[PDB]
Amino acid sequence: MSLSVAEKSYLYDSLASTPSIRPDGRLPHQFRPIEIFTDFLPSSNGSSRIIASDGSECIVSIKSKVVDHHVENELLQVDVDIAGQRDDALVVETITSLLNKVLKSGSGVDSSKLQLTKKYSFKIFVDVLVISSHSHPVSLISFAIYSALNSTYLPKLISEELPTFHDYDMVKLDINPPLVFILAVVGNNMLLDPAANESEVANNGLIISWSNGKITSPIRSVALNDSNVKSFKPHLLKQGLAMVEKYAPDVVRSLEN
Amino acid sequence: QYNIPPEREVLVRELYQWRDLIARRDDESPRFVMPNQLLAALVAYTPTDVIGVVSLTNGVTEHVRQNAKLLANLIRDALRNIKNTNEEQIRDVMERFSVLCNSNTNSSILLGKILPREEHDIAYSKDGLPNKVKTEDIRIRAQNFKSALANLEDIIF
Amino acid sequence: SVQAEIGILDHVDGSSEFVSQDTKVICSVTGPIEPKARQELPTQLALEIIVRPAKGVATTREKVLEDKLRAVLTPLITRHCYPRQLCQITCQILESGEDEAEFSLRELSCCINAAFLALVDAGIALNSMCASIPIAIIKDTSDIIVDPTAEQLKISLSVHTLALEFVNGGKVVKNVLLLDSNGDFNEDQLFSLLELGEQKCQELVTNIRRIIQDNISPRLVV
Amino acid sequence: RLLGPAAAKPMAFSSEQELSLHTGFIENCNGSALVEARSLGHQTSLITAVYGPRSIRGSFTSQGTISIQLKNGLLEKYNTNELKEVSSFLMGIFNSVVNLSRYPKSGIDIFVYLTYDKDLTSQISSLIPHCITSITLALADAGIELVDMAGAGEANGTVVSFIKNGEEIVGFWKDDGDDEDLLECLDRCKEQYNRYRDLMISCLMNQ
Amino acid sequence: NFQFPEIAYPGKLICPQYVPGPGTKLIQYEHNGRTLEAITATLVGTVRCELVSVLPGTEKGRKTNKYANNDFANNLPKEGDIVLTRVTRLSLQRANVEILAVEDATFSVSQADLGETFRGIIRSQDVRSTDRDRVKVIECFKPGDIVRAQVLSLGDGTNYYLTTARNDLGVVFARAANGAGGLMYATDWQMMTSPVTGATEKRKCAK
Amino acid sequence: VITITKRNGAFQNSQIVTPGELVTDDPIWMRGHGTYFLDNMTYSSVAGTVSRVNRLLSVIPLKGRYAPETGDHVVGRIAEVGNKRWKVDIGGKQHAVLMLGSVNLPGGILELQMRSFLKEGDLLNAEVQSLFQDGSASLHTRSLKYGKLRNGMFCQVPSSLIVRAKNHTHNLPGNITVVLGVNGYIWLRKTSQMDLARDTPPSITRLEEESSWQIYSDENDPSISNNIRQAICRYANVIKALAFCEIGITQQRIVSAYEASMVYSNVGELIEKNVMESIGSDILTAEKMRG
Amino acid sequence: TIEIHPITFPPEVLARISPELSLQRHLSLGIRPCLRKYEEFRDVAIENNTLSRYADAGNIDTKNNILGSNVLKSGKTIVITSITGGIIEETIIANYASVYPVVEVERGRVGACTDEEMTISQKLHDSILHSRILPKKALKVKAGVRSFSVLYPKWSYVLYAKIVVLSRTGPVFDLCWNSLMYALQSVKLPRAFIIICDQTKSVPLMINAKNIAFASNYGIVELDPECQMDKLNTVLIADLDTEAEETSIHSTISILAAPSGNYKQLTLVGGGAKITPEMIKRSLLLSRVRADDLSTRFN
């Protein structure tokens, strides 16, 4: 985004006060309406398209491949491609390396839920395509892969020889997909799910990962803007971190529906 | 346009508005009664006397000659007007500074012994053996070059 | 005996084609022309040297070929009389005439001669003239021979590419432009070939002058 | 760049934390440093160079722009995707420490070379606290202004960078590890940050 | 007015509110009480009192000039400063140059060639002191000459505004035929001649 | 709480002319916008409706951007600073130019430090003075009413949803002043001293106004009422709500939707898509079917 | 006839406004801008087998791939030369091989390989092959079969190289060559069985120690009477360094000298001053002593 310094001081003073007045007036625990479409790519096992309120749209496709897990290290490879950005861009490889950690085969998702024979297993290819974006999309892609993995169907196994699969029947992918949230701190107030203008005048940002009803390992604290970058008190680190522990079940109840 | 000091803005204002009223009185163009060439000349010479306006070096128009006594009286009015406006709890916060201040070797592991090595120049003798030069030898040559650099004050043929 | 033709291209200021044994190199010179931002020099002329192999793309093998050819033509051109200007000098090797992977001396010797010829046809200020020859020694007789063939290189111990500079009717040698060598040699054999290489390049410019006169003279007052 | 023939295959074989600090020894850039850490079965040896500040032609920004880049050295070559991930985390920290408002219309380029990363038995978590202490020494040698020293520590994957004697946190990084290990991981790095903080000043004051 | 330690490191507190300056910034700290405006040094060097400023480097580093490339990058040419430039481009009504040094005598070497270096423009109206409207810049400067020109208004969108309308300003070092000849020396006010070659070239001399 | 709309199975949920068809064969017409003449016959270049005003034949396209016309009160931010001219982003097909002589300078006739008081990204309002050959607009700030915006928040609406009225700016209850631009750039700020004192209530050859940089300063008002800032956030939602329901924006419909927001009495429940369709329907039905 | 005083400048800005003028003023005193005399070199300090898996002959590394290393430093430049290993299956100069270096000079820039990085990588490959250092019979693999129990009595070795130059101040073509010759003598070829390499067992590389050589660059500078006159006198500068010398000196001589009075490579560029046979013989003899000190510096 790009704003004027006159209105940057207005949003900074309005978000750092004790009432913590938000631009659109939403509460610090509220979110923006999101539209999610699933199951529309027959050539893929799973698929999802997510549309945000500000115009950010992202498409996720899921493919599968039988590979020997004794020689294949990671079974969940995420390929991120942002339109208008190079494949070797600095902002693309960071999310590519960050999503590979939130969906690591064994850590973020247990490999036992996609094993076949004692030798072979399914490898999940998560292809991400960001059509448009106005803020940090790591939280939007997590919502897209969540609905895509929960709407994925893989072929059923028939059973040391090469595995055979059924022609008609296909089993559902029962996998708990981790969730990623973005939090912005403005002076001394926490903001869950910031906007393009909120994250532009914020002091610092927080990335929390949620899996199996708990805060899982891959978390970050990357700055949301290079202008106003300030250090935060450790009491703010645990405030927003414990804040998602109260409202994330309300997110999953509305997302897993 | 003619580079007139901004301090004389009160003078050109009186002459421009008088030029406009006379141009409207006799139904003439403002340049017919006083062109921009003559306007800049009246504000520069500032003719106080009745002769300085009519006997100007560049020449005047018919309206300036007939109204010579009036314009020579206006510059005298503006000259005396432009000259009229020119004349007219520390120790309580210092102790907090000193009480907060109370809250406050391996040479190498792998490459720490090779990289921080300073310059070492060597010389080869006639037989073929290295001769390391001391840091004082290169220092003698340093001041010998700077002193001989600022001692050039004459050039011959 | 070598063959050479001048003025063969229609869309460059100067063109040339140097043929020796089996190596054939076509060069193209264009200048002075408007340089780019990163190329323009405040005082003297800028050079854009580009050589290309016969097979495959331009790898790092030809990059050192450009840097050595650049050092031969840079002192040969009066650069100071073309301030803030550019001159493109492209060398295209049609036939290598040797082994590209094991050798690269005959192509450097032909690119130097082909570039100098194209610099003459384009009308660029040259302080002197140039001549380059390849030199190698057979491990059998251990004697110095000029322009060795492709079979004579595989048996050679050390290779040489001597480039000289001639003035005063192609007789006086002003300075040794380039002498690139790789292999096994000593100081006794260095001057043993440097003296022999000076008289083989003297008859080369004498042969170059005859060639560049049979073609430029008819185009002038004739 | 030769790389050799493509038909060739690579070889396949079937408490206390020592620290070393240096600075300078580089003439290209303005300020440099070299940190080395040898503890248990893992050694770290990386070089940091700061080429700045350089005035940007045609720029009109109100404050400076930091450019941090991690480059693979010669051993334990990480993936390029994770190298830029730590760089973006390093820029998110140093954008709050380096006085950006002092250098308008100019940028600062950081070059950290993880030359020798060795393990003797995410592996990048242990190297992050060593990269932060190498840039602060290099930024101070280049005459660049930094608001207080910046250091970090490791506590089983969790990497937290503090400032102002550990009063306020500037950055937070965690990979792998366990669950509910927060306050203990903070204090394990809080006392480790002070271990790296005063050691940087002791090396930067010697001659 | 000097009870503080001699040397200072980034983060060391100096004195309360005193005024800030080069190497300090008003940072409010908290020690179980109200926030006090503390001036904190952000450079490695000694503190000086006049006006509070922290100058980088040691006294030996200032005399030996160990921070050569660090001094010019931190001290930008302000208004009225007299600098040493090099002619790069010659236009009909201007002359693009390249700032190489700046004085307060003593100077400071610029950045080491490649771009991203400070450049300026000497307008034809500010070349000479008399007849400022009609001049011939081709008779005043040549590409590759060191020119001593004083800066003017800072419209630094890309270049700087310089002037040579004085006696001690102009070409201070040049060579015949744009570097292809011998070193020339300034004789008259607009006549430069090389002793060995004997050739004369019209410049804007400074003697 | 979150409201997530879900789907499954699919990817998603006068005279109309198309480009390439014949609209008329009568040569006695004036070819307008979205129309190309050819072989004494008229064809349409875009898709839309046919308009026949006088002898001017033109096609009104469906999705049309902002067309800059002479004498339009617009709002735009500076995109770049050039040689004595600043390209401002109005939202049209190109960047509108703002010559240095089109704004009030405090120094006057007495200095290329243009970026000092007006850099890139700064928001302001002005009026279109004229147009260029390619359609680019030329703005000017020769009035005290036009100045650098501050003490508020910026928002954007589609250009085809702004109705042209007499007064471009209006004063709203709650000490709030709205600035409606025909380009679609709205500025919601607290009422200043100017919009409050003017929007609501022979030897003379004219003189020049003495205006300082007091209107170009980036320093906003120090003390803004907390009760007023919550009103601005309540105005930004109801404006984007009417734009979500393709409703024309006028001064009477801004204050009408403001009373409907008091039923919920919270500025956070307005971002939902269900409450926007209801408040939008409460205006089209309780106003157009009652008067 | 003429008498005009010149304009003086401090030595700091003298090298910036004109590297040619600063270079001529030093040679009038018999010194160089590098604070060195005419035929003075720079001391070196090397560390072989320091970054390799075989650093400790008793306690081998658990996870390492480098076969040998050499941290060379001459003056203020730093050269690091590691060597990785590979293997290819196969089915007078042709009997010898070479190395595949990846020169990466760090100067503070980003992008692909510089023209300098690609010229050193090829000149190193061309000098190793012509000097005959690695015969093709030394790359063969005595591949056995394990059944564990390994036994030893077509496959051939492929040797890579990565050179990282830091704090560059001049032409580093000679520093990378000397650092490679040191790093060559420290690598060990791991044994291979039936293909998998051995974890601990290694074999020393068969390097043709007869043809080993070292690098040394020189320069021919032409003076001038205007900086402290029919004709003039030229001097020879050994081991060029600093931006002043590399920019102004347009006539250099870089050579590879081997023991027993043998030479492996010579480049004779005479762009600047005239290269007389006097300075040709002097550069050759001055390099034979340089190669004797380097080969007998630490080993």
Image (tube, grey):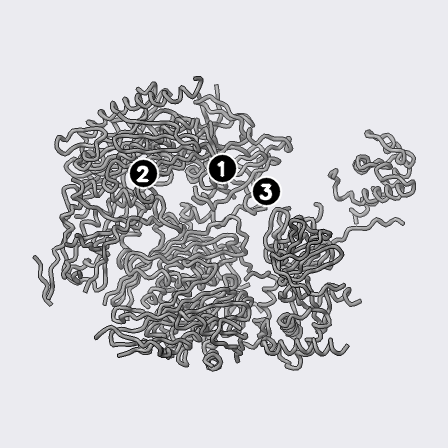
Query: E178 and E69: which one is in front?
Result: E178
Q: Amino acid at mark 1?
A: Arg
Task: Provide residue F272's location: percent of width, then percent of height.
Answer: 58, 76
Query: G70 and A26: which one is in front?
Result: A26
Task: Provide residue C171's location: percent of width, then percent of height.
Answer: 30, 19
Q: Which residue is mark 2?
A: C65
Q: Is residue E146 left or right of residue F152?
A: left
Q: Is residue A244 left or right of residue F251?
A: left
What chain does badge 2 belong to?
A: C
Residue G61 falls in image quadrant: bottom left
Q: Amino acid at mark 2?
A: Leu
Q: Which residue is mark 1?
A: E86
Q: Nearer the viewer, mark 3 or mark 2?
A: 2
State whether discs 3 and 2 lie on one chain: no
What chain does badge 3 belong to?
A: E
Q: Quadrant of the N terminus of chain B?
A: top right
Q: Secondary structure at mark 1?
A: strand
* Mark 1 or 3, nearer chain start: 1
Q: Secondary structure at mark 3?
A: loop
Q: Quadrant of the C terminus of chain B?
A: top left
